[PDB]
Image (cartoon, coloured by chain):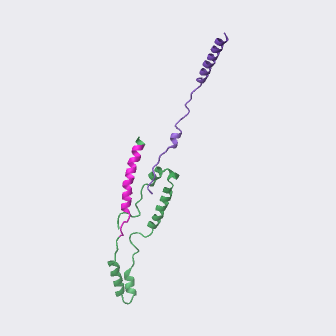
Chain colours: A green, B purple
Amino acid sequence: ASKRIARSSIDWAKMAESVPESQKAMYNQFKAKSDGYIRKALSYPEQPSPINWEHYRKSLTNPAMVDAFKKQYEALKVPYPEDKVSSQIDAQEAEAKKEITKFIQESRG
Amino acid sequence: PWIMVFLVSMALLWAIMTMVFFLYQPRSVSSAKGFSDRTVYLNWKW
């Protein structure tokens, strides 16, 4: 419902300059793998296709079933699901920070 | 006095041999080319 619409995209240019190319060729796999999920993110935007309920109300002889369907559609409005492994990324983020500090001080030495 | 002449000649031969042993040109041909091959790079958390 929030957080990440398709507009969000990190700076690939700085990331591409940082990696040692074929030494980190999994980034070349990672970008295409993330790009494939962008293709899934290309389809199915937030809102669905609107439906003209009044046309089916007038065309059908008894529009009570259309009103019941519209009422149930408005009642059933499920929100977003739950994030699963965000804590694991957060845990590896803290481990990355420790490896960042360790690599920084060794390079300083 | 063959013994004294022999000793001087052998002592000379030892002295020439030592002078030859240090007669050389040291060189320093170890540049930092191998230092350029030690690029330590962080493994990325994929």
Percent position of residue A5, x then y: 39, 64
Q: A3 or A60: which is nearer to us?
A: A3
Is residue A78 located in the magenta-colored stretch of the structure?
no
Residue at the extreme top of the image, as rendered: B1
Task: Say which residue appears at 47% left-offset and 46% top-offset.
Answer: B40
Of B13 and A13, nearer the camera is B13
- Residue B36: percent from left, percent from top: 51, 41
Residue A29 pos. (x, y %): 50, 59
Where is B45 relative to A47, above or below? above
For residue A79, above or below residue A65: above
- In this rendering, is residue A85 above or below A16? below
Q: Looking at the rendering, which quadrant does residue B28 occupy?
A: top right
State the quadrant of the C terminus of chain A: top left
A87 within the magenta span: yes
Name the residue at 37% across, 81% down: A53
Q: Residue placed farthest to the bottom in the image?
A: A61
Decide which of A24, A12 is in the foreground and name it.
A24
In percent of the image, x 59 and y 21: which residue is there? B18
Q: Image check: B36 left or right of A96?
A: right
The part of the image, by quadrant, that contains residue A74 is: bottom left
Q: Which residues are magenta?
A: A80-106
**For the view shown, which residue lies furthest in the right direction?**
B2
* Image label count: 0
The quadrant of the picture occupied by the N terminus of chain A is bottom left
Q: Main secondary structure of the magenta part?
A: helix
